[PDB]
Structures are given as structure tokens and as C-alpha cells.
Image (cartoon, coloured by chain):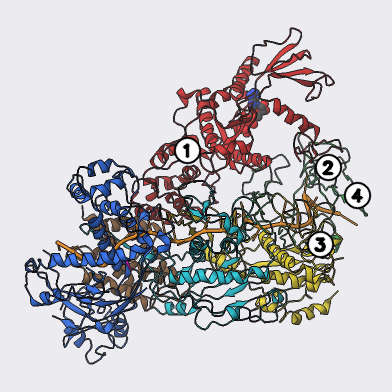
Chain colours: A blue, B red, C cyan, D yellow, E brown, F green, G orange
Amino acid sequence: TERTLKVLSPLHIGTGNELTPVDIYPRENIIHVLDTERLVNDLMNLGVELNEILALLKNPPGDAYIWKGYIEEFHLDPSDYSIYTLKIHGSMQIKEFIKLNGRPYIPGSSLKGAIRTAVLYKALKECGDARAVMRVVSKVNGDVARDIGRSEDVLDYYMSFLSRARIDRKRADDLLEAIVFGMEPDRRSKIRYEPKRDPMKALIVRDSKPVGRKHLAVYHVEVIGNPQPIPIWVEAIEPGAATDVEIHVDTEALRLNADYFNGLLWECLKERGEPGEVFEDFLWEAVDEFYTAVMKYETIEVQKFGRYTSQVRSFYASLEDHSGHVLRLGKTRRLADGMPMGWVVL
Amino acid sequence: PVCGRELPEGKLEPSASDPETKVCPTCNRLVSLGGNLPKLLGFGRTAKNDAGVLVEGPFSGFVPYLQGGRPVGEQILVKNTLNPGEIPESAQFVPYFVADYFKKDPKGGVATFEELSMASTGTRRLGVMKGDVDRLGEFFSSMDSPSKLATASRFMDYFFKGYIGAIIEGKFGYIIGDVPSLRDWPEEPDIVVVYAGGDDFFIVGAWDQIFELAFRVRRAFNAYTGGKLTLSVGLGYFDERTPIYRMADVVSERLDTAKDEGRNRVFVVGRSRPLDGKHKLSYEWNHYEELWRTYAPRIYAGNGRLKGKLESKKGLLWKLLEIRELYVRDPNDVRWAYLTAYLLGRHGLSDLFPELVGIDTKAVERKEPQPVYWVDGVLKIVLMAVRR
Amino acid sequence: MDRRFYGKIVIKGKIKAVTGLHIGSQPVIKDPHTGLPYIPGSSLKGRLRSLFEILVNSRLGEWREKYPSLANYSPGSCRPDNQENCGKFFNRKINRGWIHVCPDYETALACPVCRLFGASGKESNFPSRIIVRDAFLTKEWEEKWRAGEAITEAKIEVGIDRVTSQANPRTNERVVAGAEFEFEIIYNVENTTHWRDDIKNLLTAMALLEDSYLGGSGSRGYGKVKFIFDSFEFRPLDYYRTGKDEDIVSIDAREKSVSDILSGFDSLFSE
Amino acid sequence: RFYGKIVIKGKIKAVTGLHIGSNPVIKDPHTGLPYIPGSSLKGRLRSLFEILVNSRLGEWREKYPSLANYSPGSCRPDNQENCGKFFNRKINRGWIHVCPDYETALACPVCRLFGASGKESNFPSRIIVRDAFLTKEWEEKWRAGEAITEAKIEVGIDRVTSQANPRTNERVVAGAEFEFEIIYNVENTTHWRDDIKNLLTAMALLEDSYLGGSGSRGYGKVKFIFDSFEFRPLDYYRTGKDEDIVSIDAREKSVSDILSGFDSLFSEVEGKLE
Amino acid sequence: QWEAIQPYFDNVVREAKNFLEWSPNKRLANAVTVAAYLTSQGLKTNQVRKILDMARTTELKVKRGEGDIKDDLVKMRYLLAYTVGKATGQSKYSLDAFHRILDPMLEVLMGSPKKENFEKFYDFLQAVVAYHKF
Amino acid sequence: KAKYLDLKNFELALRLRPFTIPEEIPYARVDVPRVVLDRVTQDSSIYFWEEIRFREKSGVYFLYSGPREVFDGYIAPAMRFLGWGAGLFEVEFHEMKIDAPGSEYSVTLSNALPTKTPVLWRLLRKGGWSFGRRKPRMTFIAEGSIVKNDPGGMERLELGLSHEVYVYGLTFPLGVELPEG
RNA sequence: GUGGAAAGUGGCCCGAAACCCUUC
Ligand SMILES: Nc1ncnc2c1ncn2[C@@H]1O[C@H](COP(=O)(O)OP(=O)(O)OP(=O)(O)O)[C@@H](O)[C@H]1O
């Protein structure tokens, strides 16, 4: 199942192994990201180190101008040591895009997470009532189910359980995910997320093809919710770098082992007949519902952006005029030159 | 093939089994003796050419006095009792004591090795125990009367012929107490006494109860002599199809090695050791019971299941033997106490081995081995207990 | 009852995996001295076998006379009825899971999975007839690892659920996309009529493994193995007994879409 | 008579390690090292060769004339010894090939190169497979650590729960030469050429099948790099200062050594011949 | 929490910078305390994990890869100061404790030393690591 | 555990002096659980057949009290002829010296078939098939007892083959002065 | 003229299931 991923907004996917001002040399609004290993290896020989100079990087950061223009005293190359170049939109650190031999690519785990959130959204939406939840929670240690039965829907049950006492992270995070995607009777919370119950193992999301580096750049970020110094820059993919992707559905996993798979997604997708046929349409339409409801949040969140800018309006005018499936890879104020972050269509 | 009597002519006769393997007449009579051995009440010492003469002797044959018969040969060897009862007033009632205890099968007969090791809480292995009382020959060069020798021999022999069936059956619990408990001590154990008499005792059975029986026997004997005597015990674990002559030549070598290297020591499991004379293969009982009081209730729960901290991380204790092998290959290096903390930090179990993480100067002062040498004899017996 | 081999067709592998590969151990799996990535045979054999028996589970309804001993089974699962044999095409409790094992010889001699991946159990235990070598990293990537340009780069995921994302991360250390793993695979050939419907029966499984993944978290990438074959050659008993430097060699042009060189299987072939 | 004791000396590289078992662990005698037991080498070296002649019995049939009354099969259907299928010898569960008489096993090409017993047969195996014992590179490699074994974990993955289970294996480290040796008695000089050609055939069945335990998924893939074909005719024992054959050593590939240089190696031993 | 004996143990390691021809308990008896100070401050593992990969790769280059670590030892020496420069606020206040040991060690230990000489440093490199968790 | 002794604790283990036992014995009487295999299928059949196993630098030796002409004519060519795997064998000749006092009654150093003369001796029973038909039991004195009332217990002719097998047992002295008996 | 002569510790088993390096 070969699909094509077009990039609509600025998109940033980044590890945390950031670029450092020892790698940057801002010149003519174009950053040449250096390779300091080869630079240090070709700066001792026919150069100097004084036993310390190339290892003297406990000096304060920034200041790339001297850092080349005197160490390259018309002695080194300008950017033969650069691995690649970017395009400045907007002299400090840079969040690096997740690479692969020096090439950006969309990791399929991020795509699977942004699909599975939509799957959770439609699973709680079109099946989240007490005459569909309690019938399954009673089958797996239904002492939780009699607490569910006081409410007509499990949304209020999880709003209760979140607002209950003794709330840690490890037990309270995965409980709604367990109720939707399958559980097991264990003594911890009277259910436990045994993750092998999940039908998402019938969903395969490959990693993308390598995106071309000539549409890879560095973008400014404003977060207008606090007067804290935010000179934050992210590596990103230009809107227009149409990549490819491979993602499909294993009907030959659900079709065989249709008894042990349980949960509210499995119950909500047994309703539409054979689960081999409707699983793909369920995930695609869950995408189409969730990435429209995010706009429905966002079309009133315009004053909550802080900057009522016409770019946001001209983007929302185009957000619901697409022939594929729009998605999102990552005070709510994360903006790239005012444009939103991470919106791609498939 | 059965006996090593090993020089008959064609006199040997195939019977009492698949009748294609020719078999000596001694072991023809002996399996028939074993078929009467649960229901046997005694023997009757008569002349060698009477009716019902099962086995012979140097002077006299024997008639197996079963539960209803009335044999006479002027002497009746009655087993494990002092009341003669239903034997006539012509013969000489001679009592004799035998540690007799053995697990009856669903029929009532003697369980075999394959019938016994199926009740092993853990791996399917057969436990074999062979002991000795320590420095007893010097103990009988110190009694200066026939009366003192008679009392000091009869009280010793009554332990290894009559007390053993009491300790196996579960009695004497008021002084035995906390031995290494691999499981619950059942009503009928899986323990078959092969030969207990004089000083020594040789007992086969399921290893999870052989192990508990060794410490029960030792601590009850420590109570029984008042601490002035000790007993050495070798232990062994074999496959159920292992020949018995190897099964005894292993534990005899192990009892001799625990005999040589401190004279009052158990040999729990054959461990790897360096060759310098400082690492002893055996274990003092006050060492091993201390260690099982130390490291077993922290890491091992009851009845074949690991502790709730080590639950679902049950390949952790296997890594400690791989750590300990570095100390085995060289005693002078110091990698072992480091890699132990490198293992225990990765799983959060910071406290389960405080002795293994830091090299103790107390042992290297007086040239004693490091505290990671001794813990694996506490590890493997748990590792055989929860293996599947 | 006979093994009676004459054969050993071999394929010389070359699984250049693209988009990652994460096979796990106690992190990638090089236990020996030259620290490296490698694919350890059994992770390729088991991923071949489970995928092939998933194919046979759905396609037993039409073979069903060809491979006649397959007809003793149902396409269900022995999960509810926890008996070690039930009459369904899943049995053999390993420790808690279930795999297909014919517990006889003559029922395993005809079974279209078990005649190619081996039986077990009481008295039977068929030899697997396939030999799956441990795929070591090729000499090209060894020379390109000695010169820097590191292989087995790490990768961090997170568990960012649908809560306040305090997502606990977990590094994975997969192999770099593009890694020639110098694979080799041997199939024992016995009694020729039992043969042509075997490697043709085998490659389809690998073709499914060309569509599916191997090695770890394949639901989020980590597959795409691309078995670009090298040899397809065959080593008869006519020179294991007398080695005259001769062999019957096929062609390894790109791949097979669906068995294009089915005709060239029998090019110089009588055994 | 006796005009014998050919020494094939060599080194066997386990390209993916070995699992000659005894957690399953390798055979470790007295120093902690592993080793190929010569029993396992001879045993696999006869299973491969016996199944070769099981396939090839109906067509040789004039060479090795005692291998004609067999008509291939195993005697496990008709549960009796001496059944003419190929092989009886019911030990406890298995069925191996042993000719039940000496006069027959002077001609059976498998049986006259690994021997025969049972009742009133007593054929000696004509071969001595010395256990291979970790040549002095990897002994000194072992002295500084280097972890000569390797704990390797497999699983039984299910398909309806997709659960798994640890089945550790602890195999020998991939790549280790072992100082492999073969000693062979050269009684019956007319048999000898085909005999050592048959032993080299059985060794050439290795490097393409599994030694050592849980094969067919890795764990085998051995390689004989045998250096020195020798000879010890009848003067190496009464004397031994000189006068014995030493053959070419360096890069003798066994799939090429089998005949492409063998008759250039045979004819020097034809020079003694007595 | 932190007490001056622990930076003085670091100062024993840094002013007694020679550990190469010393006893194998001089390494371990200090390596606890070093790591104790290194765990008295924060020093989470994942920024130190870039260092250790350069050790293990050069350790495999020791195990019959080359003669020594001549040019690749510089990037072991460089990346420490690189992490120091990258570290900000709650880290550069703390990560210099890990930094002040490996630079004065590897200064003279870039004397192109033997593989048996460098192994005594690599064992100390490993020796610091576990007592982060202990 | 009186099994074997050093030479320095053997020139004075006799002659009535306080010897000392050694402990560095090169034995590994191990329990090697060998072969289990059927040519076509499984085989379970764990048959043990244990063997002895040595140390790193150890090895058997034996003695020779004879003229070196007879040694180099029969036995010394044969001791390199001897070199299933357990026939591993490399031969290295040597000389040795033993103090060995006055020869009233002294050790045999072999297994022994005596001429009816019993003095303080472990008994042995040695089988041996020896080309097929099982040799009889042939009661022996064990390694190292004291029969020196003029020994010379001849080798025993047997039956079963074409040419007779005849079993060793003739001994050679040493020096002991035993206390009484 | 060897307590011998014939005797692979073997057969089956994916280190797998799930996890957006992202939020404030
Ligand atoms: N119940 C008993 N009554 C009388 N004598 C006994 C008894 N049990 C053992 N003996 C004597 O002990 C002697 C051998 O015992 P043993 O060798 O175990 O003594 P020991 O002093 O423990 O020696 P070691 O410590 O070397 O075993 C025998 O001569 C036997 O007479």
C-alpha cells in the first residue's frame, strides 16, 4: 500500500541531540552545519593545538565569526567541512531533525502514534456509553464496571478516576488506553494493560523514504504565552517536500485470532461486520474525524494564539479542502513564523 | 547385568522382569524380597533347606515372616519392635532395628526413581544423601568400660536406625526449626531410606526433600548429642536414569572431600573453585544455615515461586553465576564486585546483595574467600527450585 | 520412513534491510568478539515459519488434498481448549504459546509446513530439511565500519499516550538502514517429486516476509528486508562424493515477482 | 596386517559457533574451556555418510558388494532387527546402521569405516577421531578474558497471544579454531583410496550442514582448514628420525582438496605403498 | 548531600593523575567515591552515553583492530569539553566533575600507550559507570 | 584417602618415617553423558559411559626395570604406536631413581598374580574382553602391595582364541622394611 | 596379543507484543 505524504505546514521531528554553536556558522542568512570531527582532525596537523586549543571548548558558546574567520585565517575551506546547509527563517543552539546517515526521514512510530490517537478518539466517540463499556468491563473483573454503571459513559468515569486520589503516573496514564485497547485481570488496578490484546499489531506503519535535504531548513519559533527569552530554532522540512510512505493493514492477523483480541476498539469494530474489511476504513475515517475536530478546537483558538494573523486564517481556509488525510506530528502557542507545526496530508 | 556378582555359569535365570535378560539367582530372590518388603514383618533364621527359604546365609537360610505366617528355625529376627506377639514359645526372639521409611506407591510397594523424582518441586532431578558421624573412632577410644561402650554404641545406633523414621515423618519439629525450607514438608515425603545404620546413612529421594532432610538430620543430631559430635553429609543430584553405582561414587567422593576439608561440613552442590587451597568446596553448617537465613527469604518465596520483586525478571539470578565465574577464573581481580552492582543497578534491586557489591576487607585480612564465592550455593538451589 | 537426501539447493541471501532493523538480546545481538550487527538464523527461520503457517492457516481450504495430512486440522486456534492436541492447526504448548507441530512422522511427512520446518514431540521429531545460516554482516560493511561511518546508530522512542505527555523514553539501537547481511540458506532435497512443491512453497513465505517484517518492533518500521538473491545454485551428490569443481547454477538477475524462473528451476535438473 | 595411521591434522573454524550440549551448556572438561568431543564429530560424520549411502545404495551395488541386500528404508515400521531395509540396531529408541557380521562389514562402505558390533561381529572402527582442543591462539585469547562462550536467547513466539519464553542456549563464540585431528588405520590397502575419499566426502557433507546441537537455524557452519596429511607406514614406529610424508598445508579447501589436488597428493603416498 | 571529601577524592584522582602503574584496588577504591560525588550531583546517563560508545568502539579497536588509538582518541578527548560547552545551568555546574578526570588522565595517556596500558583506563571508565545507579 | 604419593613422600613413606599425603591429584572422573541419536529421527537413550579426564600439564607414566636393549626393541617402538577419541598419546622417555632399602619384604608396583604367597594385600578382579570372548575374572593383587617371599608369579595362559592370550601379573621389587606381621 | 567392539546430548521453537522525542 504505497501512499504519498505531502507536507502542508512546517514540520519538526527531532531527537534532542541538538546542534551546537560549535557547528553553526551563520553567513548570508544561510547556515552551513559543520563537521567538527573532520575539522579537529584537519586542524591539529598543519595547525596548532597547544595541548589544549581544539579541546578548549569550555569557552562560552556562540561567536561563530571568530570561530571560523580566525581559525580559518584564509587557511581552511569555507564550507567543504559542512555536511549540509539550511535556510534561515527569522546565534544560538539548533534542535536537530532526526536523521539517517545525514538525511531526514519521517519515523513510522510517529505516524503510528498520530494515527492511534485518532483511533482512540473515534473509539471513545462512537462507542463510549455505559451500554457498551460496562458489558466488557464486567467481563474482566467488573468491580470497576459497577463504578462505571453510575455514569452513562466512560468519559465521566475516567474524569472521576483522574480526579481520584493517590494518582501516580504509571497506573493512571495507561488505564484509558487499557480500557479501549484491551486489558488483563491483575491485582494492581483490578485491570492492567497487557499490550498483546491490542489490534494495532495488525497495523503496519513503515518508516518513510529519505526526504531530500534541499527542503530541510531551520525555522524560528514564537511561543507567546510568557515573557521568557525564547530564541529557539528547529530543524524542519519545507512545505512542499512530497515524500512517500508505506502503511497497510494485516487482515490475516485479526481474521485468524479474533477471540483473544478484545477491548473497546475491537468491540467498536466488530459492529461493522468482518473486522478485516472495516479496520482500514475505521482508521482513515478516525483520521478524518480527529484532524477536523482539532481544527474545531483551533478555529476558536485563534484569539488564543495571541496573534490573530491572516496566515492562520488562510491556512484554516485550506485545511478542509484536501483529497487525502490530514494529520499532525506534534498556553498553547507553538508556532513557526505564525504557521502551525507539523501538518501533513496523505 | 543387575548384580556385579559377575561369576556364575549358565545357572543364572531370567525372571521377575522382561524375561530375556538372564539374571543371577541372588537378585532373583531379592526383587521377590522387595515385593514383600512393605508387608514384611520379619525373617526366620532356619536351616538352609527348609520350606519358604528365600535367602541363604553363611550358616542359615531365612523364611520371610509375613503378616500371617508362623515360621520357626529356633530364631526369629523381628523388625523394628520389641513385642514378640504372634510367634511361638520355641524360637529365640531376636529383635533388630532398621530405618525402614519409604514412600509407598499407589499400590503400596516401593517407589522407583522415576516414581520419586516426579515429585520434585523444580527440575526433575534425584537427590542422594550420604553421611557419616565425625571423629567417632576417636570417641570409642575414650570409653573405659564395657558398660560405657555398650551405652555409647546403642544410643548412637538408635539414632541412625530408629530416629530417622521419626525425623522423616515430620516429628522433632520443636527443636529442628528453621532449616532451609524449599517447600512445605508434606505428610508422606518422597524419601526412601536405602541404608542407615551404625554411624552413616544413605537416603535417596526427591531432591527438594533430600535437601530439607539433610539439615533436619543435622540439627536434630546436634540436639541429640548435645553438640559434642557432628555429622558430615554429602549431597548429589542426578538424572533419574543415572546408574546407582555412579550415584554412590559421586556422593562418596563428595563426602570424602567434605570430610577432608574441615571434617564437619556439608557438600551441597558441586561448585567451580580456583586451585590455591584457600577455596573449600564444602560448607560449614553454621555457614550455610546462616546464608539461607540471609539470602533466601529476600529473593525466594515459598513453594517453587520466586519473590515478588524478582517476579517477571527471573533471569537475574542466572547472571550472578556468570559474574561469579570471573571470580572463579581468577581470585586476585576485582571485576566481580563491580559487575554485580552493574547488574543490580539495571533492575532496581539495590539492597538484595549488599555483600556482593563491595569487596570486604574482612575476608582478605585473614585470607578467607570473598563473599561472592559462598552465595552461589544459595543461588543454584533456588535456581533448581523455580526452573519452569 | 526414510530421510534419503540428494540435493542441498542453496541460496546466497544478501538481505540489504532498508528502514531499520532491531533484533534484541541481553540492544543488538552480537555476543561474539567482533562486535557488530548480525541476524542469527533462528530469528529468520522462525519469522519464516510463523508467517508461512499463518498463510497455510488461511489457505488450507483449497489445498486440502495435496499435502493430505493437513486435512486432520481445523483453521481455528487451541487457545480456549487448553489441551496439547485438539484437532486444530495449532498445538504444542511450548511454555505458554502454541506452534504447529505434527506429533507423528507420517503426518509430518506430508504437512506443507512441517515437512519444511521440522516436527517434535513423542517419538517423531522430523528433521527440518532447511538449514538457515546465521546472517553475518558482509565484508563491505565491515570495511566501511573499520573506517568510521558507524553502523548500529541508536534511536529513541517515547510512550506519549493520550494523557499529559510525561512520556518515559526508551532507546532501541537499531541497525542502520542499508546493511548487507550476507545471508545463506540451505534446503535439503529428498525424493524429487517431494521437491519442486517445496522451495516454490518456501520462497512465497520469504515473499510474504518481503512484504512483512522481521526483527522486533516491525509494526512501526524495522523491516523491508529485500532478499536480493545471489546464487540459487544446487550441489548434488554427484560431486560431494567426487568434487570436480562443477555445479548447477541459476540466475540472480533482480528477484522473482511470482516465480518467473519456475521454468529455469528445472534447467539442468533431474534430482 | 597393519600399514597405517594416517594423520589428518587441522583446524576447524566454527563460523557461527557450536552447541555440543550436556541452561544447556557446552562440554567443559577441567579448565573451563569448551571443546568438540571426538564422539560428536565421528557421529555426525557418520550420520551424513550413512544417509548418503541410504540414497545411493541401489546404484553403487557392485563396488561394496555387501551393500546390496538392503533396499532402502528404516526398520521402524517392522519392529525387528536384521530386517532388510537398511539399518536395524534398536538401541533404546534409535535405529542406526551396523552390519551384524564381520564378513559383511569388510565391504559395507559406511560400516567398514566406523565399525560394527552387536553379537559375534566386532569390527574395529578403522578411524580415531581425536577431540579437538582449542588451538593456542584462542587459549591465550582466553587468558585475558575474551568470553569464549556466548549466551544466546531464543523464544517460542505464539500467534494468538504473541507471547514468548526464554530458551537460553549458551553456544561457543562464532569464530574459533579448535585444533582438529583425524587418525585413520590403513589396513587392507586396496580399500584405502575409496576409504579416505569417503571420509573426505563425509567431511565435505559438513561445511554445508549442522554440527553440534540445535542446528538448521544457525549454530553449525564449520570449516575444516586441514593442514598436514601425514603417513606412518611401518618405519615411523620402529624408527622415526625421518621418512614420513608431509603434504601441502596452507589454503586447502576441502571441496577442492577432495580430488583436484588429491591425486597429486595420493601419488606421493603411492611412492611408499607398503 | 555533597561534602568536601568527595571533591577531594576527585582531587586525589586529578592531582594524583597517575593511575596507570598503580594497584587494581587503587582504581576501585576511588571509583566508588568519584561516582558518589558524580551521583551526589545529578549526572543522568544519556549525556554520558555519548562518551561510553567512543570507549567501547576503541576497545574493540584494541581487541585486534589496530596498534593503538592514535587519532580517534582526540574525539574521545574533544567530546568531553563539547558536552561541557553544551551543558547549561543545572548540568555544567555538575558535569565538570566527570570532566575533570578524563582530560588529565588522557593528557599523558595520549602518549600512544599500549593496549595493556589503556585497558587500565578503560576499566576505570567502566568502573565509574555502575555506581551512578549505586 | 591413601591413594598416591610424591617421590619424596615415597622414599620415606616406606622405611618407617613420617610421610605427608599430597592433594594435587590429576583426576576428573567425570560423568560425560554421551550419545543420543537415530539416523532419521529423535533418540532419547542417555547412556553414560563415563571416562577419566586430566589436568592441564599432567599425564600417566609407568616404569621399566630392564635392559635398555629389550626396551628399545619391543616396548619403546610400541609406546609411540598407540598414538571414540580416548587414545590420546604422546611419548617422552625419562630416567628415575628410588632410594629403596634392603629387600626382605617390599612392594610389587604392579597389579599382581602371586604364587600363593599372601602378605598384606588389596585384592582385585580384572575382566577384559581381549579380542571378543570375555576373559575370566583372574583375581589380582592391586597396585602396590608387598609379596616378596621370592615372587615370580608367572603370566597366565587363557583360552578362547586361536593363539592364546596370556595375562600379565609378574612383579618387580622395591625396598621396604615393614614393622611386623 | 587393550573391562572390548559398532553409539552427533539430538529433534521443534521470530527476543517477540505494544509505545508519536513530544508536551509545557
Ligand atoms: N553405631 C556404632 N556402634 C559402634 N561402633 C561404630 C558405630 N558406627 C561406627 N562405628 C565404628 O566406627 C568405625 C569407623 O567409623 P568412622 O571411620 O566413620 O570413624 P570416624 O572417627 O568418624 O573416622 P572418619 O572421621 O575418618 O570417618 C568402625 O570401626 C566402627 O566400628
Judging by the rendered image, the residue that carries numbered circle 1 is: B288
Specify the subunit that label 4 lies on. F
Of the residues shown, which amino acid type is indicated by label 2? Arg
Q: Is residue C177 above or below residue F32?
A: below
Within the magenta stretch, is there residue A107?
no
Specify the subunit that label 1 lies on. B
Q: Residue A324, image x and y in percent?
A: 26, 74
Judging by the rendered image, the residue that carries numbered circle 2 is: F137
**Disc 3 vs disc 4: which is toward the camera?**
4
Judging by the rendered image, the residue that carries numbered circle 4 is: F160
Quadrant of the displayed image that contains ligand 1: top right
Write down the quadrant of residue E112 in the picture: bottom left
The lab-note entry on whether marks 1 and 4 share a chain reads: no
Specify the subunit that label 3 lies on. F
Judging by the rendered image, the residue that carries numbered circle 3 is: F78
Rounded to the nearest angstrom, the CA distance separating label 3 from label 1 is 53 Å
The residue range painted magenta reads: C155-159
Residue count near mark 2 (Cα–Cα under 10 Å), binned few <14, some 14–19, many ≥20: few
Rounded to the nearest angstrom, the CA distance separating label 1 from label 4 is 58 Å
Q: Looking at the image, which is closer to me, A1 or A269?
A: A269
**Disc 4 vs disc 2: which is toward the camera?**
4
